[PDB]
Image: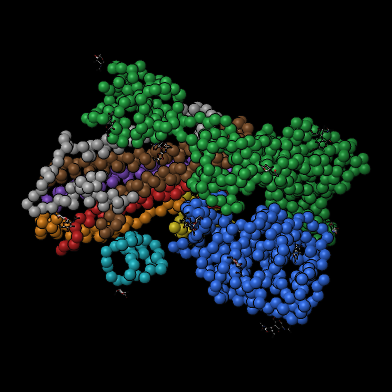
Amino acid sequence: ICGDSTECSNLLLQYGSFCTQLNRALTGIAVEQDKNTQEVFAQVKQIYKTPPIKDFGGFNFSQILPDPSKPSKRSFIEDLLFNKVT
Amino acid sequence: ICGDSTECSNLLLQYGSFCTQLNRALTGIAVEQDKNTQEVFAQVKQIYK
Amino acid sequence: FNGLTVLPPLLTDEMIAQYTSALLAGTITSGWTFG
Amino acid sequence: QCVNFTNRTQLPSAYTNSFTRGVYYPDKVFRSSVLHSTQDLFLPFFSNVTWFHNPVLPFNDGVYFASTEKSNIIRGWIFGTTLDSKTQSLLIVNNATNVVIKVCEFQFCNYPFLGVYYMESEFRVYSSANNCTFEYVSQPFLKNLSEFVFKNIDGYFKIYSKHTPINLVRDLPQGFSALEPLVDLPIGINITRFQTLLALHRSGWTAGAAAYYVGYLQPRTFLLKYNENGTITDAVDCALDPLS
Amino acid sequence: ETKCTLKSFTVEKGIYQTSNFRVQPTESIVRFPNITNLCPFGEVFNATRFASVYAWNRKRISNCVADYSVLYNSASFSTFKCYGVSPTKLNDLCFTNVYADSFVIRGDEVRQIAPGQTGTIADYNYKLPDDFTGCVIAWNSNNLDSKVGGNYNYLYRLFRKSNLKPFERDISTEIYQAGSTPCNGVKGFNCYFPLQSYGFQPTYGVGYQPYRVVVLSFELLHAPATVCGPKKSTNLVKNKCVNFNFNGLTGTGVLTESNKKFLPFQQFGRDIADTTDAVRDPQTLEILDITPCSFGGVSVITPGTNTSNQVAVLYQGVNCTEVPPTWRVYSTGSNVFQTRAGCLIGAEYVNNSYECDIPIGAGICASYQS
Amino acid sequence: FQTRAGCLIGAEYVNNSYECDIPIGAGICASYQS
Amino acid sequence: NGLTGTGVLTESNKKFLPFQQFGRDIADTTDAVRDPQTLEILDITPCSFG
Amino acid sequence: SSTASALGKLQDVVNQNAQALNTLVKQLSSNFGAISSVLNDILSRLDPPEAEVQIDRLITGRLQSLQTYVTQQLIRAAEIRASANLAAIKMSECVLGQS
Amino acid sequence: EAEVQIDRLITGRLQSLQTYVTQQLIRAAEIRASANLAAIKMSECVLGQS
Ligand SMILES: *[C@@H]1O[C@H](CO)[C@@H](O[C@@H]2O[C@H](CO)[C@@H](O[C@@H]3O[C@H](CO)[C@@H](O)[C@H](O)[C@@H]3O)[C@H](O)[C@H]2NC(C)=O)[C@H](O)[C@H]1NC(C)=O
Ligand SMILES: *[C@@H]1O[C@H](CO)[C@@H](O[C@@H]2O[C@H](CO)[C@@H](O)[C@H](O)[C@H]2NC(C)=O)[C@H](O)[C@H]1NC(C)=O
Ligand SMILES: *[C@@H]1O[C@H](CO)[C@@H](O[C@@H]2O[C@H](CO)[C@@H](O)[C@H](O)[C@H]2NC(C)=O)[C@H](O)[C@H]1NC(C)=O
Ligand SMILES: *[C@@H]1O[C@H](CO)[C@@H](O[C@@H]2O[C@H](CO)[C@@H](O)[C@H](O)[C@H]2NC(C)=O)[C@H](O)[C@H]1NC(C)=O
Ligand SMILES: *[C@@H]1O[C@H](CO)[C@@H](O[C@@H]2O[C@H](CO)[C@@H](O)[C@H](O)[C@H]2NC(C)=O)[C@H](O)[C@H]1NC(C)=O
Ligand SMILES: *[C@@H]1O[C@H](CO)[C@@H](O[C@@H]2O[C@H](CO)[C@@H](O)[C@H](O)[C@H]2NC(C)=O)[C@H](O)[C@H]1NC(C)=O
Ligand SMILES: *[C@@H]1O[C@H](CO)[C@@H](O[C@@H]2O[C@H](CO)[C@@H](O)[C@H](O)[C@H]2NC(C)=O)[C@H](O)[C@H]1NC(C)=O
Ligand SMILES: *[C@@H]1O[C@H](CO)[C@@H](O)[C@H](O)[C@H]1NC(C)=O
Ligand SMILES: *[C@@H]1O[C@H](CO)[C@@H](O)[C@H](O)[C@H]1NC(C)=O
Ligand SMILES: *[C@@H]1O[C@H](CO)[C@@H](O)[C@H](O)[C@H]1NC(C)=O
Ligand SMILES: *[C@@H]1O[C@H](CO)[C@@H](O)[C@H](O)[C@H]1NC(C)=O
Ligand SMILES: *[C@@H]1O[C@H](CO)[C@@H](O)[C@H](O)[C@H]1NC(C)=O
Ligand SMILES: *[C@@H]1O[C@H](CO)[C@@H](O)[C@H](O)[C@H]1NC(C)=O
Ligand SMILES: *[C@@H]1O[C@H](CO)[C@@H](O)[C@H](O)[C@H]1NC(C)=O
Ligand SMILES: *[C@@H]1O[C@H](CO)[C@@H](O)[C@H](O)[C@H]1NC(C)=O
């Protein structure tokens, strides 16, 4: 609103607490986003790992499991999704 | 807000784009209503008799 | 009016009635299979 | 020192397409890689532009003057209202040496020109100049397409120029090129008409290859694009096409 | 600070945003063009002859250094009233293409020289613009512009077909047809000469004596500046958040040698929303770029006042190289750390990883053992 | 062409019926083929 | 008669009581006027826009 | 891999946020009835007894803009929270068991 | 004085329009929630045994 002005700050101070609740609402929104992400994804208590040898009767999950080569440890489909949207 | 007046339009000109952002919401609302109707009713691919 | 406009809906009531008639005929004749 | 003639040459003023020429930098502000929408005076895209193969033409809002010139035959410019000593007029002469701009109550005759001698020493455009204030001297303004824009806004006379190499024979090139600002004059006159001067070889005047393109401006809105180097590379007119 | 901003004597274990900090500026930089010369104000003011109302004398002032102290300290000016700027800052600014319009009017009509004013000369002789910027000076000239024989050289208009545009000039002395029957260039009934002479005589009292009026009109940052004040320039310093006044353009930030290219006619540049990102100094004609010196929010981490009184201060989005809301105590030898969220002062990084208490951001979270 | 939504110019009206591409209104819409 | 406005004027079949001068329908929107010279009931419609 | 424009929802959410921020930051370049849209200039030009009025006009305009932006953000956050709850439910039944 | 009077008129009409738009947005959100519930109910109940 004021951009580093003493006169503007003094003039705005007499308007009362208008923007304090705005800052509170923005902080609440950010906390809400964090809670949304955490509650959507953190559905498990531990971290599991697939066995190194995989023989699932014929089904092939290589396209969905993460690839050890990539440092991001993101699978092919995840890589495509990340690259598509920017 | 002007009723076809030049002075009113000139005075409003120095307010920036309240009007663009205002009009940008009604269109979204209308598209939302159309999507609501389409998703509620168009649950099938063919028409039976 | 006074600068306000009302836009007509994309889907007419006849098409909505046609959807409902098709759905009802399907559920009477086929059941849950057509879903 | 000017006399009447007998060979009343009539220029076959044809019509042709303006295409997308006549875009100039509107402000003195640097912008890079940005799309800016500005409303000002411009030459409308795809408009009628007159081609002359020396009559009196109105000034209107502004004037766009183009020449696919060889050896720079065109020399001068005369602006005014009645083109007499009664009303203040303006004159521009770009000879082989520094260009001269004057505003005076000149007394123009029927067929003003410079005239050259074959070692050239001749200056007989006008006859008298009694009262006047402002003068200006600068470096000369001038096979090549030369484009100039003359604007008169708020007692300010803006002259914008651009020179380009050309190879096409007759029609204007279907390309885009910005016009950098050249000269600003803080002098206000009621200019409404303008002329053109030729460098005829006086030894018997011989000036027949005097061809130029003349167009008129209008106020409208453009959308210009500034590239990474701050040079306008594309423009879009607003009130021309629903897609536009 | 947290106790003051939370309104309690007890604070639980949590993170609370307190305030924000900025890097304060040091010294100041004033840069003005090297050109200097006394500006010709004597002729426009001390003029032997003054034209009529309908023929107000307009003069242009450019490429000069103007001192407004002499035009303000003198008490010879009966009225000195400005609209766009306070008179005390006239010598603190730089303009281009100054205009001075001078004339002589009656004493009672001095009130008509104002924006949005209706009258005789304010409507048919010289109409000021509604958004006028500049100043108006009026003073008494009875001893010089009034003679015992009566001065008939001052002619003012009374009749006109329509009103006058702002800053318009009309000189046509055409016969006015005041009735249905046209005059056809013949004076008679319903025909009047539009110009009339003043009755300036020394016998007249106050309000009727001739008054000399000068109106000064300015511009506000529309072109390269040419008329600066009497201020003196100074040297420039780079890589320091300082205050700058480049040819009237004021601001605060840090300057750097820019790499963008300016065409020989361009002065400065901007990218989005009046963000002046480059300047050309009027003296060296060199390109510089401006960026604001760093600032950002500050937050605290505490394990709860019930447990201890140790806090950790986090500055958001600020490079840890420069940090020293002074609180210099956390700048001597305390442990420091850098993360994607900013810089942390007062906490020690530990390599072990386990399910944790209060978070910070970017996957890094703090807790109590220190 | 005249529609319950208004008046449309530049595009011709046909008697066929396909899937809707650019919604117009009142149950009709246009597509590119002109 | 001092009441200003823009629109298209048509003939109307409304019957004013002999002492009114101009009518309206709802929300203070004029819809009919009586010309002082002829005393005829007209109808006002806002000309099209969109 | 081949077909594009298959992620419309996230793209339009990002576009809405970006355009909201863009118009909010663009609103700073309006006079709002004052003499200039930059506060330092009006501070440096005229007397504070009138700078108070000019800055008051700027303050009320910017307050209106900020309040509108905050309200729009609140509505969008509510919608996003509803969508997140639906996604969490879908993860609860469809993934961890047969529905 | 005309710009002042027009300013008062336009600003008041501005708060009126803003309030109308906000109420429309809230009502549209509620209607969207109701429509989603109706679509779900029509999905499980009409097309199968719930
Ligand atoms: C700048 O020049 C223009 C030239 O057109 C001035 O406009 C007026 O133009 C008319 C031409 O139609 C001039 O002739 C006059 O026409 C009227 C109407 O037919 C007639 O009643 C007069 O007897 C005369 O013949 C007219 O002189 C001219 N106006 C003036 C004041 O010269 C325009 O006014 C000029 N502007 C300035 C600031 O000088
Ligand atoms: C699972 O599918 C992947 C993807 O097709 C298979 O990886 C391919 O294997 C063939 C034969 O070895 C190679 O020619 C391809 O280059 C491989 N593709 C990639 C992207 O590496 C994988 O072999 C399949 N696994 C099983 C058990 O069928
Ligand atoms: C009047 O001027 C025209 C144009 O300069 C002259 O026409 C040219 O005459 C020469 C002489 O043979 C020709 O080579 C050119 O081709 C002509 N040009 C055109 C466009 O026709 C004309 O001869 C002159 N007449 C007089 C009497 O001087
Ligand atoms: C923009 O300005 C530059 C600087 O003069 C022009 O020169 C190019 O500079 C880049 C990097 O400095 C080089 O990679 C190019 O090879 C240069 N090209 C030429 C022709 O000199 C550049 O041409 C201008 N235009 C563009 C589009 O960059
Ligand atoms: C017009 O003339 C008067 C008198 O010559 C000038 O007043 C002088 O101003 C200078 C500068 O402040 C003083 O040092 C002199 O003492 C003044 N003279 C008198 C007699 O008081 C006045 O400055 C001139 N006008 C302008 C615009 O310069
Ligand atoms: C804080 O600033 C320093 C210096 O400005 C940054 O150090 C530079 O880091 C970049 C890569 O990030 C290197 O290319 C430079 O050579 C470094 N310069 C110096 C002088 O060390 C440092 O990275 C900044 N902090 C963060 C977190 O980025
Ligand atoms: C309005 O004044 C005119 C002036 O005569 C009159 O209107 C005429 O009224 C007679 C009968 O009263 C009609 O037959 C005419 O057609 C009317 N018009 C003209 C042009 O004569 C009458 O005095 C007034 N009309 C009213 C009060 O309705
Ligand atoms: C204007 O352009 C049209 C289109 O080519 C042309 O037919 C016409 O001769 C030109 N000149 C005039 C005066 O219309
Ligand atoms: C060209 O113009 C200049 C400037 O008026 C003049 O001095 C000179 O004599 C003219 N002629 C030549 C051949 O330079
Ligand atoms: C100069 O101007 C005056 C008045 O404007 C005029 O009478 C005179 O003819 C002009 N020319 C000369 C040479 O004085
Ligand atoms: C034409 O313009 C070019 C600018 O690219 C210049 O080099 C040349 O000397 C000019 N004249 C001719 C005859 O090419
Ligand atoms: C121009 O400025 C430079 C540097 O400030 C100075 O050395 C030089 O004397 C100045 N020249 C003039 C003509 O003012
Ligand atoms: C605060 O600390 C005391 C000291 O051990 C402890 O008894 C008390 O339970 C603590 N308060 C809470 C809320 O745990
Ligand atoms: C944590 O481990 C890394 C190994 O890369 C080491 O460099 C670092 O010093 C360790 N930190 C501490 C506090 O021991
Ligand atoms: C569409 O069908 C109607 C009904 O027969 C017919 O009158 C009309 O000509 C047809 N139009 C086209 C383009 O087939």
Who is closer to the viewer here, E84 or I4?
E84
Who is closer to the viewer here, G34 or B29?
B29
Who is closer to the viewer here, D5 or A29?
D5
In the picture, measured across the screen, residue E232 lies left or right of residue E277, that is right
Above/below status of D48 relative to H77: below
Which chain wears orange? C
Which chain wears green? E
User: Which quarter of the figure has residue H76?
Assistant: top left
Can residue A31 be seen in this snapshot?
no
Q: Residue at x 67, y 35 (%)?
A: E232
Q: Residue at x 90, y 43 (%)?
A: E150
In the picture, measured across the screen, residue D109 lies left or right of residue E305, that is right
Whole-percent x, y for residue H1 in the image: 25, 57
Who is closer to the viewer here, E20 or E46?
E20
Q: Residue at x 83, y 43 (%)?
A: E47
Q: Name the tint of chain F in the rendering.
A: cyan
In the picture, measured across the screen, residue I46 lies left or right of residue D73, that is left
Whole-percent x, y for residue D1 in the image: 82, 71
Quadrant of ligand 6 in image: top left
Q: Residue at x 47, y 31 (%)?
A: E22
| Display colour scheme | by chain
Q: Name the tint of chain I in the rendering.
A: purple
Q: Name the tint of chain B in the rendering.
A: red
Which chain wears blue? D
Which chain wears brown? H
Q: Residue furthest right?
A: E149
Which chain wears yellow? G
Whole-percent x, y for residue G5 in the image: 53, 53
Whole-percent x, y for residue H89 in the image: 19, 41
